Length: 293
Length: 250
Ligand SMILES: O=S1(=O)N=C(Nc2ccccc2N2CCCC2)c2c(Cl)cccc21
Image 1 (cartoon, each protein chain N blue to C red):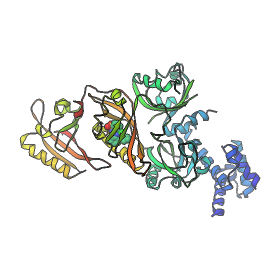
Image 2: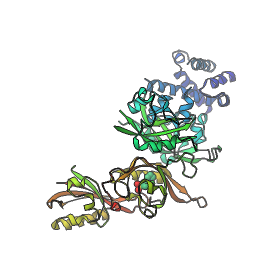
Image 3: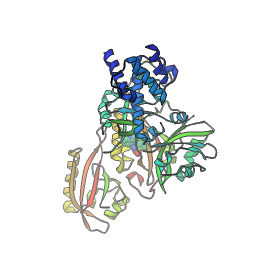
């Protein structure tokens, strides 16, 4: 009875502090999820766990075709407040924003197997490192990049990385990165000084300008989606895009955009963007826009 | 229901344990649980590689030499472990990324690390997202991820953007087209047709129109050109940002 149910908890890949404390149904759920994850690992594969799990800025999620999160990495707690035992075996739709359930579904199916999306998940931890009850759960945006794999069913194996809020940030900021503030139409309202030392624009001559005029046309589609995502979920990470340099040429960039809300009236105030300069000025002899003259 | 979900959990545990599923009579709850304890007491590097094509590596903070590199560096970069072992990160990275590398490998001020750099694979470089911490050493995982020319115009028709392929399609430098209106390079007969197309693309916001006119080249010959254009709208304010044209010869 209790003693044999207490035995499976010890034998689950969990510490004895958190395993010896769950109910019988949770033990069954975790055991079944672990066995399904092992059955899939036997398919994908034909100590150092601390290094791999600690050096990750996200968590690994193996979700079945029906939405069952049969595997969730431990560090998920560090990023979500909701820990491994409370979420493993449950449906992804029961802990994700309903306005993203259709996209989550159309990413769970199926012949390209690579998947890259943004999804909003329940988060019950604050920036002070203190975990909060599920009733006070915010929506945290997660960039999920992974693959769909058929085995014996289909599974989505993704890495979900949170997008760091520019205010509460704790990562050496490369000198090859600069900050910028925008309105909701992505027009410059503020820029950092380093843009002069990286791209060549003075922060004054960019204010009031539409950022849609300062990047290469070949990226135009790939930016709109970002904006839309940044406007639909409040956070996005763009792809590699070419921003037209000041005196000719362009510079490669990757930008993490975050919608900032006014703390007193809870209205969207502006959009803060951390831009990572990925190269020096390429094709500096070639001019593209009218501002390069 | 509690009994229905618990029974479904038990029968699913029956189906997963092989030595239990091979049985004819489904054993009682006490037996299957003991048979499951015995199955588990008898018995994620690839999960990271499957998810984001990442590989782990430990580099020294002072010299930059690697003190460990996982075998996953071969699937992600087509490079042997012998190519990475005994070498520094500064050799496996684009020359224009060493300054950025130092500012991430410097333990003077710091701890977490996150940066992007181009690593050599196979003179081809691929973009790698490196996330890790300090332990000095850096424990981090690096993961992976001319018949026409495109121009952009204001509503009036002023070149505000021109790609380099124009120098082959019409023979003009990008600076020659920029600042001037597209109808200035149009044959006077077809000029009214070009303004009519620009009148519709704005009126048919989002829709794609197509006009075919004679474009004056730098050699001063009238090259017949189909310009398919459409208005670009801001995803938030729906403001017309510009008019994107793809001017194709003949
Ligand atoms: O002029 S830009 O090259 N275009 C930018 N971004 C941009 C433009 C249009 C649509 C969406 C975006 N983004 C929102 C978040 C991801 C990128 C940009 C930025 Cl955000 C900062 C500096 C310079 C430039």
